[PDB]
Image: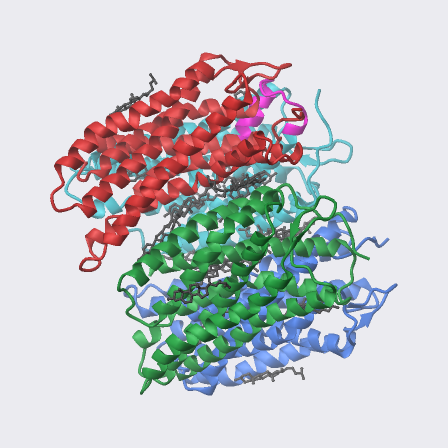
Chain colours: A cyan, B blue, C green, D red
Amino acid sequence: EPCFREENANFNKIFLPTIYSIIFLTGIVGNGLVILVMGYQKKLRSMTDKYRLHLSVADLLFVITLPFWAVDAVANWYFGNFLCKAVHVIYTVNLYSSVLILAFISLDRYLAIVHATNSQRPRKLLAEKVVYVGVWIPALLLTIPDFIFANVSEADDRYICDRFYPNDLWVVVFQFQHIMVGLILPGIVILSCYCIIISKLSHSKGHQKRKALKTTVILILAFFACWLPYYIGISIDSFILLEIIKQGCEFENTVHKWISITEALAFFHCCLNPILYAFL
Amino acid sequence: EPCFREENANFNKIFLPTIYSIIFLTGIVGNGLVILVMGYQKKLRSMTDKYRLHLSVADLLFVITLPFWAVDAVANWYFGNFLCKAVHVIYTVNLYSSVLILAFISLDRYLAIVHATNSQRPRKLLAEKVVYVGVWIPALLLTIPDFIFANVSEADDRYICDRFYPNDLWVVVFQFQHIMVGLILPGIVILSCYCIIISKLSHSKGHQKRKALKTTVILILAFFACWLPYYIGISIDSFILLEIIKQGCEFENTVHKWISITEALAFFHCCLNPILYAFL
Amino acid sequence: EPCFREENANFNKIFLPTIYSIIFLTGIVGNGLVILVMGYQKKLRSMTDKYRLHLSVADLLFVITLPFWAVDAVANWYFGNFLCKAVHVIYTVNLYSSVLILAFISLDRYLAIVHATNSQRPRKLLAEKVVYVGVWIPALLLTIPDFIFANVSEADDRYICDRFYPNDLWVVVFQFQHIMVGLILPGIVILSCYCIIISKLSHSKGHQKRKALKTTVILILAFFACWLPYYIGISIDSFILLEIIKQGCEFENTVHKWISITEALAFFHCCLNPILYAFL
Amino acid sequence: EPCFREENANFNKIFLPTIYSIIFLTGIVGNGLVILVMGYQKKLRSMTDKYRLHLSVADLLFVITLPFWAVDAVANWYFGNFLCKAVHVIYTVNLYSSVLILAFISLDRYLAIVHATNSQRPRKLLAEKVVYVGVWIPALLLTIPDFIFANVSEADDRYICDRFYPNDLWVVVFQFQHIMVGLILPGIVILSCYCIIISKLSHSKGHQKRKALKTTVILILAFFACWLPYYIGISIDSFILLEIIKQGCEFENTVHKWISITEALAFFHCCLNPILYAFL
Ligand SMILES: CC(C)CCC[C@@H](C)[C@H]1CC[C@H]2[C@@H]3CC=C4C[C@@H](O)CC[C@]4(C)[C@H]3CC[C@]12C
Ligand SMILES: CC(C)CCC[C@@H](C)[C@H]1CC[C@H]2[C@@H]3CC=C4C[C@@H](O)CC[C@]4(C)[C@H]3CC[C@]12C
Ligand SMILES: CC(C)CCC[C@@H](C)[C@H]1CC[C@H]2[C@@H]3CC=C4C[C@@H](O)CC[C@]4(C)[C@H]3CC[C@]12C
Ligand SMILES: CC(C)CCC[C@@H](C)[C@H]1CC[C@H]2[C@@H]3CC=C4C[C@@H](O)CC[C@]4(C)[C@H]3CC[C@]12C
Ligand SMILES: CC(C)CCC[C@@H](C)[C@H]1CC[C@H]2[C@@H]3CC=C4C[C@@H](O)CC[C@]4(C)[C@H]3CC[C@]12C
Ligand SMILES: CC(C)CCC[C@@H](C)[C@H]1CC[C@H]2[C@@H]3CC=C4C[C@@H](O)CC[C@]4(C)[C@H]3CC[C@]12C
Ligand SMILES: CC(C)CCC[C@@H](C)[C@H]1CC[C@H]2[C@@H]3CC=C4C[C@@H](O)CC[C@]4(C)[C@H]3CC[C@]12C
Ligand SMILES: CC(C)CCC[C@@H](C)[C@H]1CC[C@H]2[C@@H]3CC=C4C[C@@H](O)CC[C@]4(C)[C@H]3CC[C@]12C
Ligand SMILES: CC(C)CCC[C@@H](C)[C@H]1CC[C@H]2[C@@H]3CC=C4C[C@@H](O)CC[C@]4(C)[C@H]3CC[C@]12C
Ligand SMILES: CC(C)CCC[C@@H](C)[C@H]1CC[C@H]2[C@@H]3CC=C4C[C@@H](O)CC[C@]4(C)[C@H]3CC[C@]12C
Ligand SMILES: CC(C)CCC[C@@H](C)[C@H]1CC[C@H]2[C@@H]3CC=C4C[C@@H](O)CC[C@]4(C)[C@H]3CC[C@]12C
Ligand SMILES: CC(C)CCC[C@@H](C)[C@H]1CC[C@H]2[C@@H]3CC=C4C[C@@H](O)CC[C@]4(C)[C@H]3CC[C@]12C
Ligand SMILES: CC(C)CCC[C@@H](C)[C@H]1CC[C@H]2[C@@H]3CC=C4C[C@@H](O)CC[C@]4(C)[C@H]3CC[C@]12C
Ligand SMILES: CC(C)CCC[C@@H](C)[C@H]1CC[C@H]2[C@@H]3CC=C4C[C@@H](O)CC[C@]4(C)[C@H]3CC[C@]12C
Ligand SMILES: CC(C)CCC[C@@H](C)[C@H]1CC[C@H]2[C@@H]3CC=C4C[C@@H](O)CC[C@]4(C)[C@H]3CC[C@]12C
Ligand SMILES: CC(C)CCC[C@@H](C)[C@H]1CC[C@H]2[C@@H]3CC=C4C[C@@H](O)CC[C@]4(C)[C@H]3CC[C@]12C
Ligand SMILES: CC(C)CCC[C@@H](C)[C@H]1CC[C@H]2[C@@H]3CC=C4C[C@@H](O)CC[C@]4(C)[C@H]3CC[C@]12C
Ligand SMILES: CC(C)CCC[C@@H](C)[C@H]1CC[C@H]2[C@@H]3CC=C4C[C@@H](O)CC[C@]4(C)[C@H]3CC[C@]12C
Ligand SMILES: CC(C)CCC[C@@H](C)[C@H]1CC[C@H]2[C@@H]3CC=C4C[C@@H](O)CC[C@]4(C)[C@H]3CC[C@]12C
Ligand SMILES: CC(C)CCC[C@@H](C)[C@H]1CC[C@H]2[C@@H]3CC=C4C[C@@H](O)CC[C@]4(C)[C@H]3CC[C@]12C
């Protein structure tokens, strides 16, 4: 039996737009400046800069989308139907593309350090062609469900832009797929690559070969640190869905609020990328 | 139908005076020392020092005004009528002068970096004459409404020093004007100048030409960061005024409290300026 | 008409002992090590070390006293009458001696910088003889009221070790005296000395003459920063006592809790001194 | 008369698993990498590395145990009886082994600094043989009570994996023993060794002999700082047990919540060790 009394808190209606607007401004300015400096001009000296440019493009699209999130968080979504689908589409594109870009950065680091003897053609070919196919096509393929399912439906004057499925089985399947492709699958690749790099990092002593990984590792740990609590919340909610953590109706509201605040902090990570790009 | 039950919380009556007193002490000491070192003696080597001196003068006047704010925040305003007008006048003068001084600093940086070939007479003339007219006269012109409208009126033993207008149309018009002249109009100029500087900052390599902007950019970002949440709150309240975010009487109190605390943190920025002047 | 319903919160009964115990350990270890290194051995190279040794002795005595505070904060004071007087005596001695030691440090800095031409005998004589008389005798003279007035009296099984006076006039007079001799009187001397030093610090350029003040100024600002909120709270309470801020019975409890927590943070400063002594 | 209404808060059921999962990931990765770099390869240049390897092994075992804690914190313990005993066994092993390893590090530092004249054979023999016996055997001997007493018992559908004793005398005796062997006994040894080192550290001037203690002292202070509040909470609870702090039924719940959160932060220390190992 579904519960009731689900509504947004008064403090949240003012706290969330502040976060969204700060992320709006910071992300737009930083990503635009990074794109202008890197792509338009000639500043790509290393191979990580191209992946960082892809990251900047995805983050710029998402932060452009954000003001609709900020407006919706206050009162409601009652300004169209196609805009809900569009917002969900860029959301999913950025969400599934940033992690794959990070995994490609880790793979490039592994190929550059472990097989430094003769590997420049593999790195170049992988970089160009595989980043295009591997990092983008799957993002669109996972946005495919967004076109079909995203919609806005009112329920006694309650207009919500929310993905709707005929049954809860679709809900749990898609949440588990989100977890698997967002955290577990690329996390294993990143961990394996960096562990092998660390094991092989026992030649001569500290040098540029040892200090070249600092920026990449800081970026990766920051990206995953701002995302972990949201993943924990959604995993707990999905477990509640399959009659495993049945504990009453007062747990679902708490986990939902956890999910919302942690989504806001993930968008904070989306802004945190160019900030890391500033310090150098 | 206007709501009721508007009163200050017991915790606020002790939290606000603490912030006001800390700002009192820090701002007075720092601004006085900066004025004494810079104006009275001969320590103006660069051109940013004169604008910083103007900023120090404005902040010193505001922090001198502050103890009346601290006294009012506790119980009430029942110690005159002309003092309310005076307090509002220096408040508005500082509020509309600091942003214009920052915009002039940004303009000077743009003229110094982009057109470094032959530009010293434009910088000197602009600095002196335009800072006087452009940065001050408009501040007084925007304090003009304060003389007319600021007043203290009791309502069943409720003495409030608050600007009063015949209709809410004046309220929304003046709030929108405050937003436009405080955040949007100078922010665009600052962003354009610094973006053009960044685009043109691609000659030779890192040097004093690249490290001269650090203090100015830190000052500007700090100034705007301590002000953004207050602007978000007032924008939301103004939207509530024009029957757009009608959501009940429990949202207005929350946004009012948001506005108060964020005003206190803005005064914290007013103190944060000389602190930035200390580290060097 | 005095109000009722005055009792300690359940969370406070566990929060306060934690702070007291942390301060116990840190202060005892740091002050003991500082005394052992400085007094017993020969490590006094400068003239600030002797004043710092006096500060260490006073702080060591206070932190030795602290566990009685920690025990009292939990349940009650029912383990004697002479111990209450003793605890109040060392409390007052440390409280009125630390500020005077800081003022003497500031005076020594002023004499060392402004009159560096011929001043070593004034500094030595002042240091020894005036620190003894000026910094100690007045502390005992202000502890004189503690012997007379400190006592423990039960009121329906409520044993409180609290200073008792026949009238509230004594209460307000002694609170105002505490404020005047704790913050205003030495603060003016410190501010005047450092302002004159800053005005006279315009010879040659940055050197040891400019970097010798860093530790002293950091110590002084930390000392006053951990104390300001408590002084604000007691000033507000004293004003409530003289029928000035009459606002109901719900303000006194809030200001009392403010006073308690801020006292704990002041003891945190008492521990913060040797920590500043560690970094160098 | 025992009280009632003991249950976990809804917010705790989501806050605790987040901490447990973060500690899971960070501890496993860091400790595994440290073990792989140090033990498997040849990177033990100093004598502190062996004790740090022992610490890493113990922390790795505990963080492996942790996911059962995370699962239990949500709903209940209803997935066995032998697993409760096992979890308690590794918990106690790590808890009583980390402090002894720290004490051995302090003893090695004392022997290396105070008796640097002729002491290499004592350090080697002590290191190997005494770390094995002294640091391990007692840990197992103190886990001996865990085998006997750890159990899961339901009480009206309340399955709790909790140590059970016939009387409260056993409870207070074992809590006092835990405090004595966890904080007081090794703390005295560490303090004595470091105080004697500081007293003897008055030869020549600052050098490697003075900078070799930084990492060890930082590790020790961090270890004890993340543990002190939990010890304060358990001491207060044990005092409540022996009819000393009888203050009602509303104090026990608060101290229990204090204990839980502080346990989580102690596990945070368990993760903080390899982080300290990263910065160098
Ligand atoms: C409050 C908001 C507007 C502040 C924005 C702060 C961030 C986003 C700004 C401040 C400093 C800026 C960076 C400063 C320097 C560089 C290095 C250059 O090679 C690329 C541009 C880049 C990377 C800028 C990106 C945008 C940037 C990071
Ligand atoms: C049809 C719907 C799904 C469109 C949404 C996806 C769009 C926004 C994506 C898909 C392919 C993407 C492009 C793929 C490759 C490049 C080249 C790179 O150097 C900069 C980014 C850029 C130019 C991307 C921009 C964003 C992009 C156009
Ligand atoms: C000065 C800057 C920060 C303003 C830009 C931030 C914008 C995007 C945010 C701040 C507060 C938000 C407003 C508050 C929420 C609503 C409710 C909706 O019924 C009308 C749109 C409206 C009124 C929002 C528009 C977007 C908004 C104004
Ligand atoms: C998800 C919500 C709670 C936001 C969390 C943001 C925090 C947890 C993230 C964002 C920025 C991150 C930090 C970015 C920079 C540094 C300094 C570097 O030398 C170590 C990593 C460290 C210390 C990161 C730790 C994790 C971090 C602090
Ligand atoms: C473990 C530490 C080091 C990282 C930070 C974890 C905790 C402290 C942070 C991360 C996410 C944060 C939570 C985000 C979501 C919620 C739920 C909401 O209803 C209250 C705020 C609250 C409760 C925040 C409390 C603090 C929080 C849980
Ligand atoms: C608690 C309160 C009183 C502390 C005040 C702290 C601030 C305001 C003080 C502490 C250090 C001081 C600065 C220290 C050094 C300089 C550099 C000199 O070229 C101008 C004076 C100036 C700029 C001082 C300004 C005031 C200052 C910034
Ligand atoms: C009539 C009412 C509005 C008066 C309020 C505005 C007053 C306080 C303002 C207006 C003009 C201002 C002056 C304009 C220019 C200078 C020169 C500069 O090197 C230091 C500040 C100083 C000296 C300003 C001090 C403050 C000032 C006198
Ligand atoms: C450290 C102190 C002395 C610096 C200045 C403190 C001031 C700002 C503090 C301390 C004394 C306090 C004031 C004393 C006088 C009054 C008048 C009364 O009707 C309202 C309370 C009020 C307004 C108090 C508010 C807070 C207050 C003004
Ligand atoms: C408005 C209320 C919440 C006060 C907010 C104050 C905060 C948000 C402001 C005040 C001081 C500011 C900081 C001042 C100094 C630094 C260090 C510099 O290297 C980067 C900018 C940074 C990091 C600023 C970030 C924004 C900042 C932290
Ligand atoms: C987005 C981050 C990085 C910058 C800080 C934004 C938030 C966390 C800060 C800035 C302004 C702060 C708020 C200022 C005003 C209010 C409303 C008041 O009723 C409760 C305090 C509260 C709620 C503060 C909570 C935290 C706050 C919102
Ligand atoms: C948790 C508790 C026990 C930690 C105690 C930390 C503080 C008090 C300890 C840690 C480092 C110690 C300092 C380290 C170095 C010095 C410099 C020497 O010339 C005098 C001793 C002195 C000044 C020590 C004083 C005590 C000290 C500051
Ligand atoms: C009778 C009551 C009030 C006694 C309480 C005050 C006692 C504890 C005070 C008063 C005089 C003080 C002494 C005065 C001078 C010195 C010399 C100095 O190099 C170290 C501290 C030392 C040794 C002080 C120790 C503490 C002291 C003995
Ligand atoms: C292990 C370390 C931290 C213990 C030392 C801290 C001591 C001083 C603190 C911690 C908690 C405090 C206890 C809690 C409060 C009471 C109530 C009183 O009716 C008996 C004394 C007693 C029981 C306190 C004794 C002092 C105490 C134990
Ligand atoms: C009274 C309660 C709230 C405790 C307050 C403690 C705070 C406010 C105090 C204690 C320690 C102090 C800091 C100690 C060290 C530094 C770093 C130095 O480069 C500038 C001063 C600064 C930044 C001090 C600021 C004030 C400070 C942060
Ligand atoms: C102004 C800033 C920079 C310095 C810190 C000031 C404020 C934020 C700090 C200093 C003292 C702190 C207060 C100490 C006393 C109280 C009263 C108690 O019932 C709740 C905790 C509370 C409310 C603390 C809240 C935060 C606090 C007021
Ligand atoms: C979010 C999680 C996965 C991040 C894990 C961060 C910590 C545990 C990682 C990040 C940096 C890593 C360290 C980086 C460098 C070294 C030095 C080498 O001589 C041993 C491995 C060691 C000691 C690594 C241990 C594990 C480590 C400390
Ligand atoms: C029977 C029960 C109690 C077993 C639980 C204790 C186990 C896990 C403990 C007891 C003895 C321990 C070993 C003792 C010594 C060493 C050698 C050292 O270089 C690495 C750790 C290692 C290899 C330990 C691993 C963990 C260990 C096997
Ligand atoms: C994506 C990563 C963070 C997941 C790994 C964290 C794991 C160990 C944590 C996160 C939340 C926890 C879940 C929440 C609590 C329960 C209740 C129990 O009735 C079933 C197990 C289950 C469902 C837990 C399994 C362990 C769990 C999933
Ligand atoms: C028990 C719960 C509250 C967790 C507490 C964690 C805090 C108190 C611990 C964990 C990490 C520790 C810090 C680790 C690193 C440093 C920097 C070093 O130069 C001084 C010690 C210092 C400053 C430690 C202070 C104590 C510390 C901050
Ligand atoms: C003394 C300072 C410097 C170190 C940190 C001590 C305090 C502030 C920290 C350490 C442990 C923390 C507490 C851990 C446990 C509890 C009890 C729970 O019901 C509320 C959270 C609360 C209340 C935390 C509040 C803050 C806390 C007490």
Task: Determine which quarter of the picture holds residue D10.
Answer: top right
Quadrant where the N terminus of chain D sits is: top right
In the rendered view, tell whether residue C200 sits above or below residue B23. Answer: below
Magenta-colored segment: predominant secondary structure: helix
In the rendered view, tell whether residue D186 sits above or below residue A16. Answer: above
Labels in figure, total: 0
Task: Determine which quarter of the picture holds residue C274.
Answer: bottom left
Q: Residue at x 60, y 43 (%)?
A: C74
Q: Residue at x 22, y 48 (%)?
A: A208
**Residue D201 covered by magenta stretch:** no
Ligand 16's quadrant is: top left
In the rendered view, tell whether residue B265 sits above or below residue A148. Answer: below
**Residue A239 covered by magenta stretch:** yes
> Relative to residue B16, is residue D236 drawn left or right?
left
> A272 or D195: nearer the eye?
D195
Residues rendered magenta in the picture:
A231-251
Q: Residue at x 57, y 79 (%)?
A: B134
Residue D64 can be seen in this image: no
- Residue A111: where, in percent of width, then height? 25, 36
